[PDB]
Amino acid sequence: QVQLQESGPGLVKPSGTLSLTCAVSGGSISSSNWWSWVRQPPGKGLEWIGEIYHSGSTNYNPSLKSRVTISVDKSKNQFSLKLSSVTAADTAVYYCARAPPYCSSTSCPDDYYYYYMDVWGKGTTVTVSGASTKGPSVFPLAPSSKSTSGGTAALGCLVKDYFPEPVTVSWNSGALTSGVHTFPAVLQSSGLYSLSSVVTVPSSSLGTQTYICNVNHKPSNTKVDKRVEPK
Amino acid sequence: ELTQDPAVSVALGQTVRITCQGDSLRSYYASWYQQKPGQAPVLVIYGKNNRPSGIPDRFSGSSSGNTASLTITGAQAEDEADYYCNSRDSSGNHPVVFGGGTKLTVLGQPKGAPSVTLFPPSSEELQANKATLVCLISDFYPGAVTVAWKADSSPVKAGVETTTPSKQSNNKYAASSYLSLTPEQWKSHRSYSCQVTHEGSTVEKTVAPT
Image 1 (cartoon, one colour):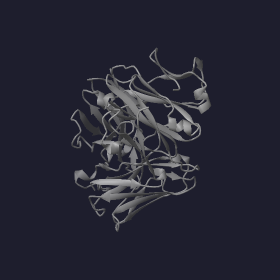
Image 2: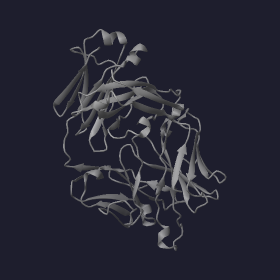
Image 3: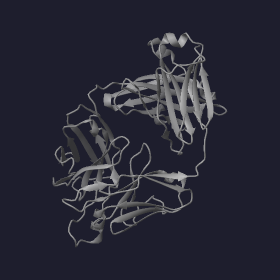
Image 4: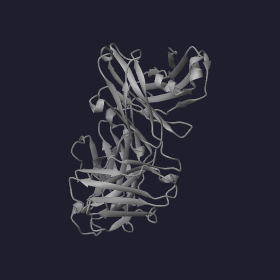
């Protein structure tokens, strides 16, 4: 109840079946709530998919009713999502959330006509594509102090040619957070993604401190820890 | 189906009213969400005029008949985001419907020149018989920019990949451009240049093989 987390394939071939699961931690699935699924295609709005009760009753979006099935696994404190006959228009970021109970009648107390979703997951990216998963190649970007302020330098990591989205970057196992700027990816003409992550550090530390970028690419189950040293 | 305005603008310190219209709103209350680029939606209004903890009281909600309104009194820069209304349908088995969204622009924010950083290819990539030039652009406002590449003193135009501007956490914008070359091309020229132009002014950074 306190936290929800999605987990899925990341890539689905056309006409395949999207399969997702939301693990509920900190609370029980048998609560009087409607466990919901929401998606948002790239550059578009929010779209409600469906919901399920802890007894198994469901309610679906009429435009997706013919392709969706939402289940609840009381033995694992989870609820899942299935979406078949996928196409390119099903590429989106999918969220699991929790909605309150309500009344469809006309004589309930006032607090039964609200609707909202106050507990959300972190979301997961699913891209419907016929291409294959490609892990990243990480190269260091040696320090440069010309574009920064007095007594600082800029060093970074280049994450080249991966598919699909996304990748996350951290520095020194999260111990280095000030001055970090990860830029959004570029879609190269080859269909592969690439981005860079730069961090600003004191130029007086370039010879004494170790700088390592931690690149994580979940769709390929790959993690790289690249050391960045001066020229 | 709930209807919103696709774009609304407000000046710093003034009041704005975002409307949400739908026949279902006669039966169920309307909730509101705020979403900034690259983040998940955040609940700001449960319904009526009830807000979660952490939401500043400059946000307020109301509804009457078939319409609902989110009101932001005294808009600040951190209120620049998208806003979605959300409720429950009144027909059938009551599915959940969303509004199309409203992109809220805040006027009067300060301008800013782009900060440019250009990295040459690394020794590891060259040894792998590849070469990438990385031009990183950040902190420019407004979010329009043009990037041009130069081999020595000549335009190249081939092998260039540039991203569209995206909004940073400080409402300024960032972008990046990549030039892919062969190791032979990198060593057969004396320099390459990344030229970034913004609001009529240009910043030029140059790298050289060494």
